[PDB]
Amino acid sequence: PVNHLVKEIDMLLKEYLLSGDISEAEHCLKELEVPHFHHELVYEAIVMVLESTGESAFKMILDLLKSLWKSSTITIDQMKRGYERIYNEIPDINLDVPHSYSVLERFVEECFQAGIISKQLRDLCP
Image (cartoon, rainbow, N blue to C red):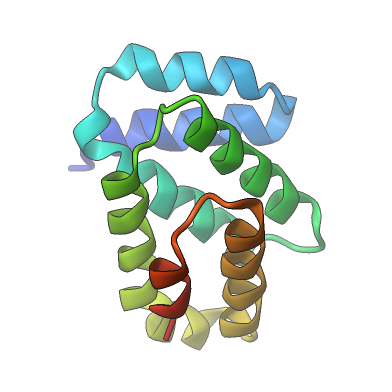
């Protein structure tokens, strides 16, 4: 069966892509009280980006992760783990979604330019 937190994080991310309401997404994540599982949010969100068409999800998810990083809602370790998961799976993801390496690189670079990931995590992108 699917982990119920995975389900709540997927719902949260979908409601945010539908509404654009960053504040509601932050509040809904906080209500879960699972700061130990915030890597799942980072991972699920970047997968949505990679699977989307056009530029809109990329931008919405960049804005979400920027906001959640600045409000201290996602911490460094959680950001690190989530990105590491993507880095591990990008070979499999790219098998199904051509040009994902290229989208991931642009996403990683924009997160770096926004100041929300370290140069180290930046450079760790395979």
